[PDB]
Image (cartoon, coloured by chain):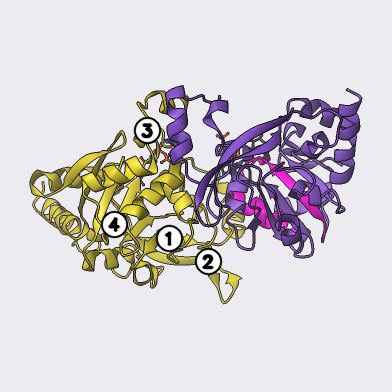
Chain colours: A purple, B yellow
Amino acid sequence: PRTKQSITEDLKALGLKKGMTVLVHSSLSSIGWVNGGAVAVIQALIDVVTEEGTIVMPSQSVELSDPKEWGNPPVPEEWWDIIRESMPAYNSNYTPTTRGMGQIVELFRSYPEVKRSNHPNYSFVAWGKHKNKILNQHPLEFGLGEQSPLGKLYIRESYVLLLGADFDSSTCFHLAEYRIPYQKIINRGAPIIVEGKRVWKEYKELEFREELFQEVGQAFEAKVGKVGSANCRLFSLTEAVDFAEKWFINN
Amino acid sequence: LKKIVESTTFPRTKQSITEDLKALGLKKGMTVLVHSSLSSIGWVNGGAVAVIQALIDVVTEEGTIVMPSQSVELSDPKEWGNPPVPEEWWDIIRESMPAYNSNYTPTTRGMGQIVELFRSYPEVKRSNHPNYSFVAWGKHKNKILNQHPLEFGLGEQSPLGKLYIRESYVLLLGADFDSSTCFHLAEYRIPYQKIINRGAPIIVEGKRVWKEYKELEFREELFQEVGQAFEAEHNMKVGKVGSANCRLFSLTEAVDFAEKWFINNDSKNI
């Protein structure tokens, strides 16, 4: 049976260190039965990194979008306007995370000390010393690019711990797309609270290409180890990003 | 979910759920214990948060909404069996089990998604029991969750003790009687009593400390029968909230009947 102690240990062996700054992606199952569930993995990462470090996690809520673009699953076209009209606004304090984000994030986002950026689709949660300066501002327009959290991390010596998670979800990559010659700008929409009032606001965002994210990560590796029974790759954010920029450009 | 979306005529919204709740019988200032099933409602735009707000919209800031937020997994591994765990692990398990914390210990899956989200919703409080905690929002959330002792704590002194004294209602939103936590309270007011020893991770003096306490060995398997008997002659509002079948009834009235059904069935029964 995996344990807090077990995991804390496992983590260091991988390379996590006190006072470090990491964006974490993860999967509870991939680790194999832990005595304590997600509260076991969280308390571990928290003991390794220490209050000197900074724990960061994506807490996306992409369901708060225009139903015209939904497809997993779709929804009758006759429901779009009524959906847009009655959709509850985003609120970092309670809007749940998309399912794909995983079980660790859903618990972490309401874990003591953790904070959440105010983006209605691409928010992040942080625990640590630099949680505020990394979430303070998060402009709706271009949720994850310069001025976003994944932007304020590129400027800090930061690492990306993939716990039981592949590269297909190394969100950081997204920053790079904001930095290459190719960029398809699109209007998106999300229910939001402006001046203490609900409003459906449209904004500009990039039409990402996340599929290429595995290929990019692939070529990026061309540390490692195991937390419980999960294949964990621990790299640096700044480097990880830079490569994508090059990968995309020359592609 | 594709099934949940395809079995739904039109989207269930905060407003349409608010309407159904009022038609059903839920009113302003009412204190109500809720047992839900988010899926039984049909696709709802906003999912759980939309259902929570509809509950708040109806019951108002003068009303009080309570929900059971049990974390039964924080128990002695021996009693486990869904699935069971190798005995060779029953010791490092009691040894390394994260202690219970009202601020983060995830509710047991069977409690529902709505309750899991409701527990960390702005202004919702949670009682201090490691297995049978409750969460409440509203006018009376403080006097209901306040006390919660480890021992028994689902009987007198637990929040059920506070929902019994002051007018309270139970709301089965897509759930049946087998989920009516209020009945457990009656089990502490009857002649029959099988007393078991339980254990759980807790924090005392600011240090984790595996503690053992006494508790009744509940017979929740009967609740479905108790509720169906209660329905023979007791007032109960029935009606749909979206595509889910619901019933709203008196908690005090339900507990009392449960007691009698139990008393006369273990004494008068063959």
Work out whether residue B72 can be spotted: no
Circle 3 crowding by C-alpha within 10 Å: few under 14, some 14–19, many from 20: many
User: What residue would you read off at disc 4?
Assistant: B32
Chain holding disc 3: B
Structural distance between the alpha carbons of marks 4 and 1: 29 Å
Q: Is residue A44 magenta?
A: yes
User: What residue would you read off at disc 1?
Assistant: B198
Q: Name the foreground residue: A19 vs A95.
A: A95
The circle drawn on residue B202 is 2
- The reply to whether label 2 and label 1 mark residues of one chain is yes
Q: Tags 4 and 1 in contact by the CB under 8 Å rule?
A: no
Q: Tags 3 and 1 in contact by the CB under 8 Å rule?
A: no
Q: Name the foreground residue: A91 vs B32.
A: A91
Mark 1: amino acid: Arg
The circle drawn on residue B42 is 3
Residue lying at the far bottom in this picture: please name it. Answer: B205
Mark 3: amino acid: Gly
